[PDB]
Each structure stands twice: as C-alpha cells, then as structure tokens.
Length: 10
Length: 175
Length: 99
Image 1 (spheres, one colour):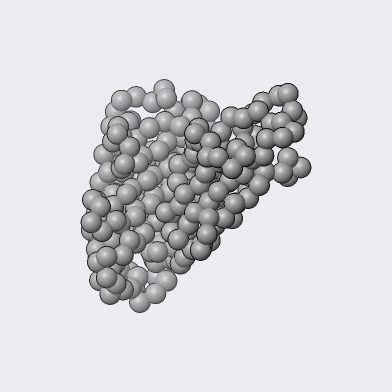
Image 2: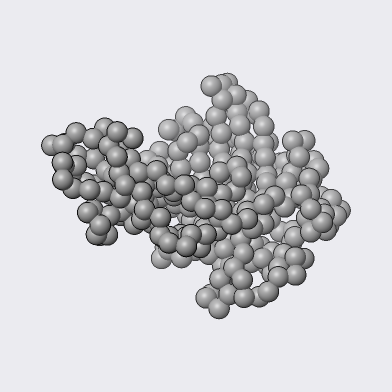
C-alpha cells in the first residue's frame, strides 16, 4: 500500500 | 525475524521527449510485489507476486492514483531542482525516493524511513524520529525550510507508523 | 553522480549440459538509469531477453537483472554486452559456468 502523494513541493 | 516493506520511485526527465519517465516498485523483504511504469500501456499499478493478485479493484485504483499523483509532484520538482542547481534545460535529471518500514518478528513497528536523492546523491531525508528533516546541501535546505513550516513530517509519520506497518503485516500473512 | 555498471553473468541453476535453466546478467552500481544490456550467444544478440523492474541500492545506484532461457553446451559461448554513457565501448562479460 503506497504512501499518500506528496503535496508539498520541493 | 524482522521484515520490511519498501517502495522505490524513480523519475527521469527527458527534454524534448515527453513528460518524465516514472517507475515505482514495491518490496516486501526481497520480493517485489507491485510495479508502475509511466511508459507501459496499462497506466496502472500491476502485481508482480502471486499473493497480491487477490487484492480488490479499489486497492488497485487507490494505489494507481496515488503513485501517479506522486509522479506529477516529481515533474514539478524536476523543474524546481534544475533551477536550484542552475542547470540547463537540455539535460536529463533524476529524482529518487525510497520509503518503508520494518516490523519485528512479532510484527511490531521497528523503524520507518523516507529518503530522496537528486542525480544520485542525497537531497532531503526524514530523520529517525519521523519528525524532523536532514538536508544534504544548500538546495535541500531551501526545501527543508519550507517543509518544516508546513509539517509534511506529520503526514509521513502517520503513514510510516500506521498504514505501512498494517499492510506489511497483511502481505506477510497472505504471502 | 555518474557511475559505471558492474556486470555479473550466471545461470539460474548450476550449469550441466543436457538440462535447462536461464542465463542471467545482473547489472548494478550504475547512474544514470539509461543503459543497454544484451545477452549474446556466440556473439549474436539473443532475441529473447527479459528483465526486472528498475530498482536501486542504498547509494541510489541502479540495478537490473536480464535473463533468458537457454540450453548450455560444450561449444555455445554466452556473454552479456552492456552499453552506458560512462563507457567508451560496450563492455562485454563472458559467461563462465564455474561462476
């Protein structure tokens, strides 16, 4: 089960 | 014995050749069980082990949307990171990320991790505490300053200590 | 950074003429991901050649496993030809059944 998508930009 | 579930993401830019290439693989110990490739024709997460094929359509849907959304974050990031390092638009560059968790023989949470790299070298990683970040350089520090103000560590910690451990245990039992 | 591939050629099962299994080429320790690997039979590219999904080790360098079914004999020579931006010429490693 993959982690939720990263919404915070680098 | 302890066990581990780990996911490996790779985004490679290709100037003048379409959107970046995205590949995602999932592992339970030394066994790869799922995979995603932006260049394949299905455009969905696919099983690579027998014990995972039993998962429902909702699982495949959810996991497919989540990896794809991550791939989009990576393409914005590939641009951002090119500017931080002040590189040309013609070169191809890479963003890699590995994340997972370890459970003990009794399946209890042992460790969790979320680390990424830019062009094969460390960039930003979440510390053991899953509450703070370690920036490998100046460029990553810029990211760290933004992230330490937006609490992205809490989002990862919830996954690494919750969802990660619980599914790893499901996979271990079904496999 | 840019790192050059390590190439290991080996059969899935211990080599014994008259039996069968797969010839494997494991490439690892390379960066970037762009790479070309071919399994050769007496210098010709074998048409069949499967491979694993792109993964990487702790140091971020990539690794790929390329394999194909084959019938090991006395005469038939086997090799793995690899091409990568870090090389001037395609590196070739011959299969030695004792390894």
